[PDB]
Image (cartoon, helix red, strand yellow):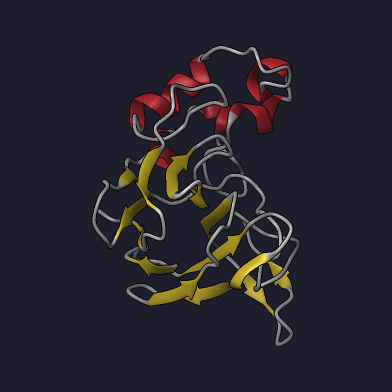
């Protein structure tokens, strides 16, 4: 499957793509403002994620640091990124269908649209100014808006036992972005697409 990753932000981002135990495609790349990078994701990929990283520095070997979404200091991510990270999430060719969503469960750094480029389903978007509106206690000094699990490490926010409810913090993310997951047990906003659809992830769509 192809994923065109487009940076419409006025700032550089370093795109990242992983399924948690491996890179997807090269795993990461710099995207200056306006640049597009197309990756190939193997059919059947379960639990893939794409995200933006901000304020990165990498040496000539591809080792370094980012302020949001850092994946073990690598340009080419093999693991998931450090919160806060707005997440484009997908599982492809799952009993003949693809499933896509956006999640704020690991916080929010950069606004995102995640849409099919082929027929048969809708896209999802979280484009509101979550960083600007972020509750004081969730603001990450390194940049972005943390989720409450990251900040407070409670069973309720982290849904450790599988029985949590919405919270004042989750409701903030949900108010700003109704079509993204705001906590683990949120009413799903997952879209079913035809198996083997292709996609575009756009940072700063609006």
Number of labels in the image equals 0
| Viewer-closest of 157 and 139 | 157
Q: Residue at x 73, y 21 (%)?
A: 160
Above or below for 47 versus 117: above
Above or below for 106 versus 157: below
Q: Residue at x 48, y 73 (%)?
A: 39
Residue 54: x and y in percent read 54, 61
Residue 166: x and y in percent read 51, 14
Which quadrant would residue 165 be assigned to in this image?
top right
Q: Residue at x 52, y 63 (%)?
A: 43
- Which residue lies most toward the front here? 95
Q: For this view, does 150 lie left or right of residue 40? A: right
Which quadrant would residue 71 be assigned to in this image?
bottom right
Above or below for 37 versus 199: below
Residue 2: x and y in percent read 42, 70
Quadrant location of the N terminus? Answer: bottom left
- Which residue lies most toward the bottom here? 60
Residue 133: x and y in percent read 39, 33
Q: Residue at x 57, y 54 (%)?
A: 48
Q: For this view, does 35 lie left or right of residue 87? A: left
């Amino acid at each position: 499957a192809t994923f065109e990753i487009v940076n419409r932000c006025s700032y550089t981002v370093w795109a990242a793509a992983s399924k948690g135990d491996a890179a997807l495609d090269a795993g990461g790349r710099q995207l200056n403002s306006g640049e597009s990078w197309t990756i190939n994701v193997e059919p059947g990929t379960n639990g893939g994620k794409i995200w933006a990283r901000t304020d990165c520095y990498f040496d000539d070997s591809g080792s370094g640091i980012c302020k949001t979404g850092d994946c073990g200091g690598l340009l080419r991510c093999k693991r998931f990124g450090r919160p806060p990270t707005t997440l484009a999430e997908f599982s492809l060719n799952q009993y003949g269908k693809d499933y896509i969503d956006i999640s704020n469960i690991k916080g929010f750094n950069v606004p995102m649209n995640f849409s099919p480029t082929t027929r048969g389903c809708r896209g999802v978007r979280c484009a509101a100014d979550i960083v600007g509106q972020c509750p004081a206690k969730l603001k990450a000094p390194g940049g972005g808006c943390n989720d409450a699990c990251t900040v407070f490490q409670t069973s309720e926010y982290c849904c450790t036992t599988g029985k949590c409810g919405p919270t004042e913090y989750s409701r903030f993310f949900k108010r700003l972005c109704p079509d993204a997951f705001s906590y683990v047990l949120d009413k799903p906003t997952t879209v079913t697409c035809p198996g083997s659809s292709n996609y575009r992830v756009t940072f700063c769509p609006t």
